Image (cartoon, rainbow, N blue to C red; front, top):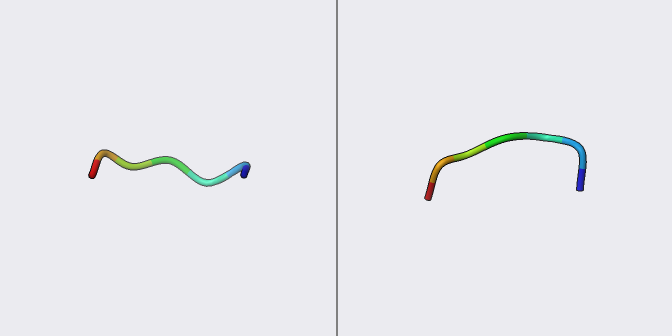
Length: 7
């Protein structure tokens, strides 16, 4: 994970 968004 470790990334962000939002989807």
